[PDB]
Every structure is written in C-alpha cells, then in structure tokens.
Image: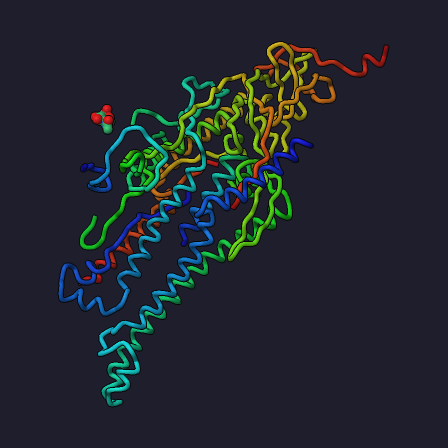
Length: 215
Length: 49
Length: 227
Length: 71
Ligand SMILES: *[C@@H]1O[C@H](CO)[C@@H](O)[C@H](O)[C@H]1NC(C)=O
C-alpha cells in the first residue's frame, strides 16, 4: 500500500483571520503580504495533488478494453478485472475499509481525476498487462497469449520456460488461490490499510487543530 | 513533500513492475518478481505483487 | 546500419526545432527560476510594511522620535521583519529539499543511463533504452534519451511448443510462429523467422503434458552430412 | 450560459458532449477555447482501443523507430 495524494484542502486566509469584518481586515493589510503568501503556498500543493495521481495512473496512451471471453489459460482474474455491477471486486473491498465538512474559510476542492476515472486507468493498466504483457509500456501494444506470457516471465528469474507448461495447471491454481486469500486477509483483518488511513487521519487531525485555535 | 516522495515511488513501482518485470531485488515483493497488479484505493494505490 | 543512422541523425534534428519553435519547452527549469525569484521579491516588498509602527522606513521613526519611545516602534518592525525573513528561510529549506531530490535523480539518470544502458522500465524515456546524452542548461540538465520503439506489427499464430517424435520442443530464444503454412521461431521483438532446426530448440519430456503444442518436423543439420 | 458541475456553478462556458484531451482542469473530471467559444467538457482518457486477445495468436513487430525524447 502506498499513499499518492492528500485531500486538496484550501483555506482562505483573510476569512479565517478576520471572518467578514471590515475593522479587522484593514488591520491585516498592515502585515504586508502574509495573506497572499500563504494562499499561494496552499494552492501550490493543491495543484500538485493533481500531478501525483496523473503520474501514478496516467501512464498509458489509450484505454485498453478487456475482451469478452476470458480463457486465460486457467488463470482466474475475476477478482481484479472490473465488474459492471456497480469498479473491481477487490477495489470494492478497499473502498469500504476507510472512513473518509467546511466551516469558515476552509474548503475542499474536488480532485481533478474522478474516482470512476481513476478506476478506469487501473483497468487499461490491467487489460494491457493481461493481454500484451510488457509491451504496452514500450510502444505499440503487441498481444501475446497469457499462458505464454507467464512463460516469458519465468524466463526472467532464471527458470527455463518448460517448467511452466509442464506445471501449467497447478501453477494456475496456486495463483488463483493466492488471489483468493487477499480479499479474505483484507476483509477480515482490520487495520490492513494502516498507511492510507494515517494520511487521512493526520491530515484531518491537523485541520481540526486549525479550527480549535479559533476559540 | 512526504507524499510526493511516495507518489514518486508509486510512479516508479508502476513503471518498473506493472509495465515490466523488475530485476531489482526486493523492490516488488519478497521473492523473485513475476508481475504486479495496480488497484486503486481511496487516496493511494495497492499493488498485488 | 545505414537507415538506422539516418533515423537517429534525423531524430536529433527535430529536437532543436521542437525546442526552438515551441516556447514553454523548458517549463521545469523556468519555474525554479520564477518561484525562487518571486519569493525573493516578496521578501523585499515586506520592507515597506508598517506592521503597526508609525512608518515603514526605519530612518524616519529614528529621525523624529526620542530613543525611549522610538524603540517601542522599532520593536514592531523588528518583530515583523524577523517573522517575514524567517518565513522566507523556511520556504527555501523546503524548496531546496525538492531540488536535492531532483539533483539526486539527475545524479542517478546520469550514472544509470549515460554511463550505462539501463534496464529499468520507463526510467530513461518511453521505450527500450539505447543511450542518453547529457546537455547542460541554465540551472538544470537535459537528457536526450535515444530509445528503441517497435512498430508495424503483424498478427501470427503461436504455439507454446513443438511436439516432434513425441517429445516437446521449446524455443531457446524465440517464439514459435507460423505464417499459416510454415512454422518458425523468431526473436521476440523483431520479425525474423527461421527454420526450426535442433540447435535453436531444446527438448524435455514427451508431448502429452503441455497444452497447445502442434505436430511439426524439426530438421537435423547432421543428417545431410551423414550422406 | 450557466452550467452546473460537481465543483461548482460555471457560467460563461458552453457545455458539450464529445470528449477531448482536456486543456484547463476544472475539477471532478471536467476541463475547459475552440472556435471563438469556451467549451466545458468531460476529460477523455484517450482513444479507447481494446486489443484482440486470442489464446493462440501473437503479434510481432517488423520495423522500429529509434527516437529522441528529452527530459
Ligand atoms: C448532450 O447529450 C445529452 C443527453 O443525450 C443531451 O440532453 C444534451 O442536449 C447534449 N448536449 C449538447 C450540447 O448537444
């Protein structure tokens, strides 16, 4: 698990410090450009959260589409590939395991890449690596049958390819089974998304102190 | 800046392990790497090495 | 060789054109100049603020006030010019760490791509890497990642192994490819098929296990020499 | 005109339907001149092409282009 972005929160300086007062502002004008300076800092990192998600996901040119028939040599991808019932299955469990309001000057600009887009990039990244393998990252996406791809990755770590075919049926079962335990280990054990939850906890705890200080 | 250090690490783990098979030791999961699968998340990313 | 040299020579040509014509081509280097100079500007503009004293020019508050009372106003400037100078320093210590993160990335891209051919995917340009060329710049560095990109693909029919004499035959370095009528092996990234002799396949076990193989003939070069 | 988004109320742009590669990010998936008018549309991820998977068919390139990006 890795965080890639925080909430694009933004705060209006003068409305926080003064809060719709004419007497206070004309004082705040004496402190030079502190108000202008912070406001620029906060929209400097708000516009950067859009560059973070635009780098992790937007790595591909065209949005590949997974085929209708799924004959992946015995490998069962039902868990990761998208399900049109609603976004993928495992992804749907991830969106349930987190617990993600404005008062005065505070706000939350919405992220540029909507979640049903972010969920779409991660489908092309899935349909290229299932069908094409390495190549959709290097240029024109060449297709290669999956059961043959894993043979060409076994040839990576130093295992001659004969091992796969000669064990294809079992290997597919281990892989299919290993994927199964994931959602179980994810669903059962709470505190499985410790990393993403902090970046939500901290960044929201920090906002809380900002408002408490108004009192 | 702590997140731009992770966003850059995820931008690498996707280019180095989803878009290829990485030879770096222990970069993508304990063991010799075979492949990886992105999965979106609320504000992050989840790899299935 | 001759064509490859032309593509490379030509590709280098378009660079200066794309660089000269399209302004905003050095967006990255220009910001680090813009920001870091914009930030200095605000530091000086802050010298003209009252912070609540009678006047923002330390000479006048000093020119027309007795020392006991003056330092009460001078204190309101010092307490401000300090907070505004210590704000500038902090934003630089943060901004410099963003550059030491890039200076370290360029120190790597030069050691990993100029001083060698990097196998990392998508580290040095989109595509399989061939080489790279440093170029200085005002305050940065510019790499010219010369990469190999395939094109003009054609569909073929594949088969994981070749069952010959009951034994399977797996390709040593290649993929078993057929133009419909004749089967071949070829390097996996550039169409160049060849006749399936024995020295480009290796054998293992009978051909009942692995699904998808086809029945074919692997010719032995030793036999035409026995006769 | 007046057009409503998830980010807010956007007046001055004429909403359209065909998607483009987006120019001026606005928010919630919506971006924003094209022929003397300001158009506000949905981002496109790019041309959607799903490649023809088989269980027995590979596709191998026959020519390349060595190209020079910058960085
Ligand atoms: C876009 O499509 C919707 C639904 O089909 C339609 O109501 C609307 O008029 C269209 N907008 C334009 C500008 O044609």
